Amino acid sequence: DVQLQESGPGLVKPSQSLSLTCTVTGYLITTDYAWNWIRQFPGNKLEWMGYISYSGFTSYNPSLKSQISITRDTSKNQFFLQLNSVTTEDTATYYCAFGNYLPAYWGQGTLVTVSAAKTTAPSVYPLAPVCGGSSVTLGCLVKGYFPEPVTLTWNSGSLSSGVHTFPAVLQSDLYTLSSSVTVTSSTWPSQSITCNVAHPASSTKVDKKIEPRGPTI
Amino acid sequence: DVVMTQTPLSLSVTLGQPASISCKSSQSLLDSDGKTYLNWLLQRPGQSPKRLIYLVSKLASGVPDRFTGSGSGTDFTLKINRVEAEDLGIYYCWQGTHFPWTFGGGTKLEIKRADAAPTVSIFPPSSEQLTSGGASVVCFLNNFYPKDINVKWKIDGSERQNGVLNSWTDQDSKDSTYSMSSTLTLTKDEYERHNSYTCEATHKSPIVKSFNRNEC
Amino acid sequence: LLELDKWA
Ligand SMILES: [Zn+2]
Ligand SMILES: [Zn+2]
Ligand SMILES: [Zn+2]
């Protein structure tokens, strides 16, 4: 099979340089094809940035010429993207892809935020239902972190159905995110449900068990 | 640079009905080699874009014959013969005939279903947040349709839109519904000075959910 | 096995 995996810093300061790696598996980048970079801005806009061919020739989007460089390391079967002196407008999801030469297969994409704001760990709060059916809805609230993304799962991911995780929203340099999970009443509290949150940026991993509320007055 | 434009911006199609998206270029995509390099792309919620169509009509390996591409010059069309739920997401047209290669802005395909009121859940601040000196009240509106919904927060009867953060999911292909979270954040001191906390959902007679501090 | 386009 042929799989592409992007990797790199999720947060870079303005005026600094951006650096991304695409690791290719299942095919040698020296054999054939063009190896592309493409980004998607917030709002869904897609932009082709450029490619490096199997033969090592490069082609760049004229809009980016004096900023961009695409290189490769044939010993690690990797190709790279570099933008010098980024600005906040370079904030986007970056994708590696390959085609012959037009892109035909895409990577998983990696988010890069360009900002001056400071990396901040999340507070995670359990949301237990009010004392007042056949199903019950629990929640998790994650506040005051930066930058995106956080990884939120229920029971380390074993809980999948009936989960709704709401897109993070930025306010005053800090993100808020929430998630709800609906299960049958024969499931909880008879069985423990825990919200798990991972924030790679701050090396944070925290767990929060949802405990039933006590009786109301 | 070659401008790609799509219409409509959003298409609401009933399951089983055909859907057609339009794409236009600011100049002819017919190359001097005879071929026309017009491509279609699909991006399902939370996923990377996938190739759907190349050379106007050719299907990428794995794509059902339900999908038909056509057109020429500067006018192209993507047709989905029997729309299924998993087809929902964003469709992009893009050109490879001219340099640099450029993409259309996208068209969202949403599944049309019967209207549905939200299931509303309210959550007082957690003991953990309260102890830290903050207070967030959370309202979940789950599994509603259409997407356009309004939430009013009332504290001791008084409406309050200050310090409210709202967030919608994309459409769920399981039941073709949407969900949204509304979070009202106050200081603990403000929170402890009022009694009733109520969120009301009205939808494109409110569904109301409420609790009283002095009952917790 | 991708077929070639004009750029290849
Ligand atoms: Zn594989
Ligand atoms: Zn749901
Ligand atoms: Zn007050």
Image (cartoon, coloured by chain):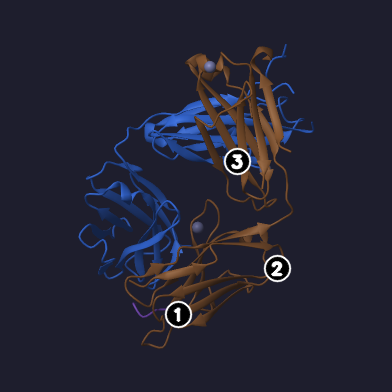
Chain colours: A blue, B brown, C purple
Residue with the mark numbered 1: B74
In which chain is the residue bearing label 2?
A: B
Identify whether A129 is placed above or below B5.
above
Where residue A107 appears, x then y in whole percent?
44, 57
Q: What distance separates the C-alpha of mark 3 from that of mark 2? A: 28 Å
Question: Which label sits on residue A40?
Answer: none
Question: Which residue type carries mark 1?
Answer: Thr
Secondary structure at numbered mark 1: loop
Density class for disc 2 (Cα within 10 Å; few <14, some 14-19, many ≥20) is: few
In the rendered view, tell whether residue A173 sits above or below residue B111. above
The residue carrying mark 3 is B180
| Residue C1 appears anywhere in the view | no
The residue to which callout 2 is attached is B17
| B195 or A214, nearer to the observer | B195
Q: Secondary structure at mark 3?
A: strand
Chain letter of mark 1 equals: B
Label 3 Cα neighbours within 10 Å, binned few <14 / some 14-19 / many ≥20: many
Q: Residue most toward the right?
A: A134
Measure how far apart labels 1 and 3 are at the Cα level.
Answer: 39 Å
Q: Amino acid at mark 2?
A: Gln
Q: Position of residue A8 (x, y in %)?
A: 34, 46
Q: Quadrant of the C terminus of chain A?
A: top right
Q: Position of residue B203 (x, y in %)?
A: 67, 44
* Residue B66 position in % (x across, y down): 64, 72
Q: Is residue B29 left or right of residue B128?
A: left
Which residue corresponds to the image point at 43% horizontal and 38% vertical from the top-left? A170
Q: Relative to A197, say whether B92 is above or below.
A: below
